[PDB]
Amino acid sequence: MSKCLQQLKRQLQHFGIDGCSLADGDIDYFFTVTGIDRGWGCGWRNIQMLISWLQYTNPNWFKRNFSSGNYEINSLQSLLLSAWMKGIDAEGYAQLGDNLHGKWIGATEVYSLFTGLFVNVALVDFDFRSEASASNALFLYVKKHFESSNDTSNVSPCYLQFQGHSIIIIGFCSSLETLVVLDPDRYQSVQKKFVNIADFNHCYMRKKRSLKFSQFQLVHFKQNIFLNDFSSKLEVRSTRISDF
Ligand code: NA
Image 1 (cartoon, rainbow, N blue to C red):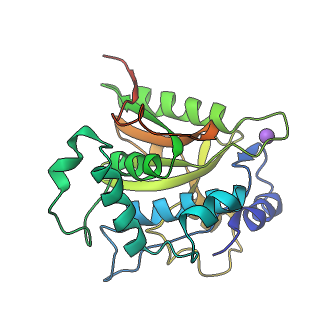
Image 2 (tube, rainbow, N blue to C red):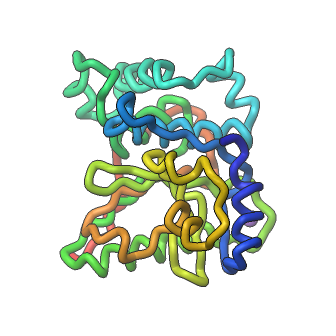
Image 3 (cartoon, protein in one colour):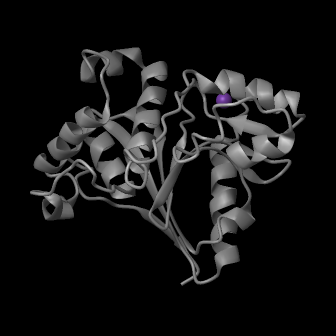
């Protein structure tokens, strides 16, 4: 689904869901297919969505990195290996020699790949004893991330990781205190007409009670989106938010 922020804004207005702040620019939706890349493709599909956001917001960066406009998963395997070979992620050598096809990837690989593309990546680690506290801190940070009063084009989507699954956060809904998300493992519940608000919510909204995890990893791009060199970003350094 191409340019899915324009249509999603219309659906939010149609269902009367107020208080939504979404990422700037636009984004394409990428999804896994059951019996093909379902169960390991989610992280790769989420990287594809983040690439599409960069594509809409800086075409020059996109032309420079994807000369044929091709960022299929095979292109991403080259970029991930390239980042490891350039010294990004101190522990990246531990995955040299693996098959990159079929490989589950996480926030560290998301950081490594985009850092190798000279993208300025922020990584936030939510690590709590209390499950309620973890979602409280996460939801507040994400809510503040998407809040913007001035006309900007640098509010990026977020990659959210929990328990091996990952999704893209494209906004926050303050009337419901829910994440607005693009989940690559829920293609079956998108490719049809939404008539009831309940089906829309199950697809695009994540309440705190739907994310009963005590650990989250969050990746997004910074206000200064692009780097001149990643020599200072070789080590994966996250900011840790915790109650212990
Ligand atoms: Na803005």
